[PDB]
Image (tube, rainbow, N blue to C red):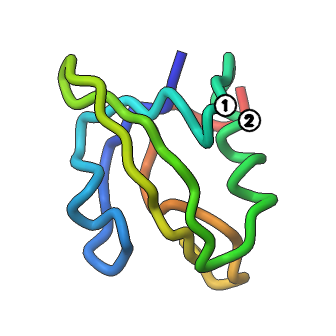
Amino acid sequence: DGVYVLSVKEDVPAAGILHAGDLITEIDGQSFKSSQEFIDYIHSKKVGDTVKIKYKHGNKNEEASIKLTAIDKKGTPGIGILEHHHHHH
């Protein structure tokens, strides 16, 4: 159904937009069955980009635009959250 937010770094755009315990359901108007997609989509975008995230805070239908970044060191494109899911399973 969607990626569950587990943590949010201090040095990222969504540092205050997305709070722990949210459920990112839409990604640029794109819904995904598995968690992988979310991983791919981002993994395709470029750093500093601005994607549209539609999350759920408890039960409220929110949404916002986040500016990607290198959640690692290889400059990979990411949002900077930790998911509850494990591996690419």
> Which residue in the structure is indicated by mark 1?
30
Q: Position of residue 6 (x, y in %)?
A: 32, 43
Q: Residue 72 vs residue 23: left or right?
A: right
Q: In this picture, is 20 found above or below 2?
A: below
Foreground: disc 1 or disc 2: 1
Classed neighbour count for the residue bearing mark 1: other residues with Cα under 10 Å, few (<14), some (14–19), many (≥20): few
Q: Are marks 1 and 2 in contact (CB under 8 Å)?
A: yes
Classed neighbour count for the residue bearing mark 2: other residues with Cα under 10 Å, few (<14), some (14–19), many (≥20): some
Q: Amino acid at mark 2?
A: Glu
Q: Position of residue 44 (x, y in %)?
A: 81, 59
Q: Residue 51 vs residue 24: left or right?
A: right
Q: In this picture, is 86 found above or below 19?
A: above
Q: Position of residue 36 (x, y in %)?
A: 72, 35
> Which residue in the structure is indicated by mark 2?
37
Numbered disc 1: secondary structure: strand
Residue shown at the point (48%, 44%) measured from the top left? 53
Residue shown at the point (37%, 40%) measured from the top left? 63
Residue shown at the point (26%, 75%) measured from the top left? 10
How far is disc 1 from disc 2 in space, using C-alphas?
9 Å
Q: Quadrant of the C terminus?
A: top right
Instruction: Tell which circle, 1 or 2, labels the residue nearer the N-terminal end.
Output: 1
Q: Residue 89 vs residue 65: left or right?
A: right
Q: Position of residue 4 (x, y in %)?
A: 40, 32
State which quadrant residue 45 falls in: bottom right
Numbered disc 2: secondary structure: helix
